[PDB]
Length: 116
Length: 94
Length: 286
Image 1 (cartoon, rainbow over the protein chains, first blue to last red):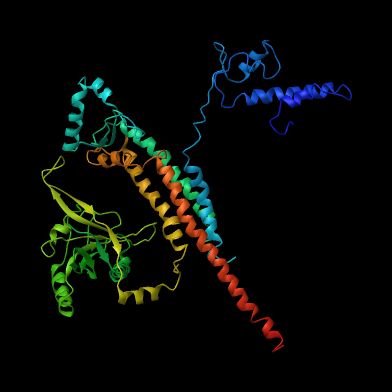
Image 2 (cartoon, rainbow over the protein chains, first blue to last red; image 1 turned 60 degrees about the vertical axis):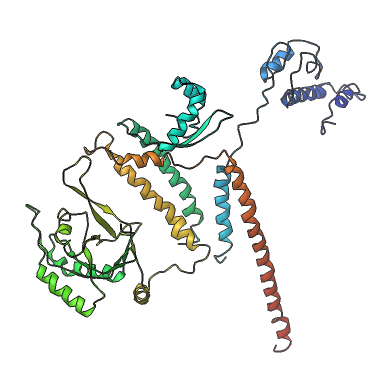
């Protein structure tokens, strides 16, 4: 269930620990999900108020959300998570082919004319 | 004055830098194209002009410093790309 | 007015042999001679030459001599042995453009109207074509003198001919990187041509040596071109110059993908023509 996107059914299994305590293990599984959602809060989302993505992990309203909202972006505003969905800087690169393909075209002429 | 990145001024800036109204700057630039002192194109709905060629002027010993330095790292760019040539196509011809 | 010059390898060799027969003076002598040839269809041709006796004392270096009797009768002989051949101008050995070569040309313009000079090389080392020629132009113009005259270089190359290509390609016998395939262009203009642009970039650096310290005349008519080179410097990679570049790469390499695919099956068929001569030959002969 951690392989696909499913997160709720993961914590339904954190409602279902049958065998022994398993306490130190699921708390690391808490922690490696906490940065994962704090990772996956950074997708193309709109304005979210301080209730919806405030309850996507577990928490009601502590200052723990300010720990996440000052770790990454989605700036603390008037009940708002600001979206810096830019993804604009990287394209229009002719040079990266123009360095790499000029290597590759010579490699075509190596195994074309000269005897090997 | 503008670099070769854009040199794309608007008619409002001409109305600012020459304090002349909007309904005459189109007549101003067609005269400039006809005499031949500038060679560019004219948009009208986005209110900009794509100036391409300008008349060459004169300059002092300070503008050669810009032409020294913009030329100078363009020297090693000819060195850098040809460095791939004689090192990768080396065994193609001794 | 003159498109280009055409120099044959005969006259190219017909200076260096004269540079050897005067090379015994040791101290100083420039090889100055008379250049013979025609010009037809606006292209300057060079065919034949000889050299005229000439001396030069270092103090008061404005006293030259051309023994014109040696200029008359020997051209009178060469016109007699070849009426097609005529005068085309003159030449000098040209290490570094000596001073008499402003009025050597004006001394002997009474024979050729466009009396062109040719600067040659005696110590061959460069990455180009060490044959220089100028042209004579004068000006009652901008700033220098009331009488102003400065030579201007017309483009220069070594022209060939069918009769001499037998002898030219016979005298080499050393190296000749023929068989123009996928790699003749790689070296005649892709190894060398990028380093061709080296010394053209480096040449304007040599003019740039006057920023505040060099020679006293500054620019006036040199910078209008240099202002244009940085202005006509090509288009940056933001437009569909990105997109139309990947367009043709997705078109030119398709033909390369087809042609390489063909080359496999051809040589595969040639493998079968060699197994037809191996298994069907061992049982017969042994």
